[PDB]
Image 1 (spheres, one colour):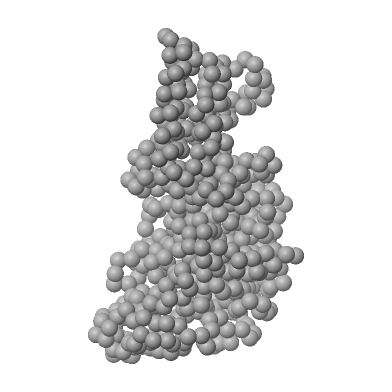
Image 2 (image 1 turned 135 degrees about the horizontal axis):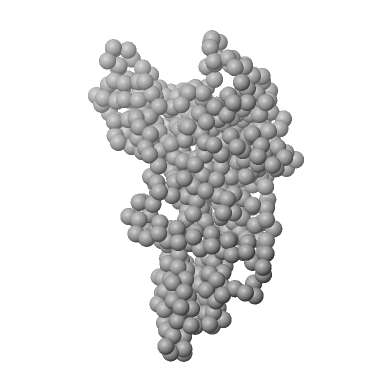
Length: 514
């Protein structure tokens, strides 16, 4: 319990230092299993739990020396916090000066002063391993960079057709706890963010027991260590006050921002259940509040003397009251988000996984990220996805028509388009999250699989143009290998299917002569 204050806040804050990681909180940063409150468009009050342990001892490694000039954001030491994440100790924003005192390498609890700064005025400021920040105020930076670098998820359909930029905003149908899809989980463990902030919301019956003691069992697939060691969990149980629940995304995003400020890429994942709020013109103003939340996502040049970049990418769950999706909460979210991954019950029923509707999803980041793909992975990345999408669009038009008149009148050419689009769906869009190889698809593998498919397309259309029956192309032996390539770990073996496709078709050009 702290001091009273007048005007849009009783100074609603969060603490930021060692032991944010592996920890489980509520909407206002009190630990696992803490109590009840009430709201205020002005003020709020609390009860009895802390946030970061004062008894715990941390190894502090000094990174600056007496006489160093420093600014807000400068890194003055390093604390090895889990086996995955080094915590970087930063001068809080608004503090500038000369370091007059700094702790030696040793072991200290968080309340110990580990540095002292003399400001230009002459005021001595005392620095600890943690800092406080008002959750409702965006934590500052030098510059918000334009969308440029993709957040690589390793999921083909997302990275290729509906990319997320680092610092970008994405929505997906919720709740995350839904067992109908596993993309939500793939996103958390595979995205190339070092740190994950997860706001598991609603959580009923067992949806707080799933998130209880299986997450401690969860392995981070990139290290073999527990995912919790690079995660901060924020819980929103149905038995929590609506004021803490409302506040949770501000607490979450502030902790995210705090990890960007160190130079980390951070993924913030916000769960949502049937109307997660009733606290906080009073339809339009809530919309405006949400925009501001989402506006705190971004990749930034951080505060500090060194040039340094970090990001918060936001993935928000969308779960309308009636499963309508013409409800306010979804239309509001979709007005601000740049990416929508349309999880589709009809795709799931057919067991097309991940169940992302390739016709109703969208990303506004394709142009933003193309240059990174072209320069680092493949100069044709963008021409290739466009081509594959145009194929999927055509297939969709054809299927509509064939719904009306049936398939018997299809020309060879249209049958070919359907054959190759089916291969695109089955061999590329579909991905096996339960397979030891296909659970992750590196960028290099993604473009090579695409070249294999599009080269098959080119060759199919050329062959048909020279009178090769489609039936003969449909049973080309390479097709079966193309269908299995998602399971191959050696990318050079996948690449070699290009020549193999080429020669096989030659054996067909020659079997038909002209």
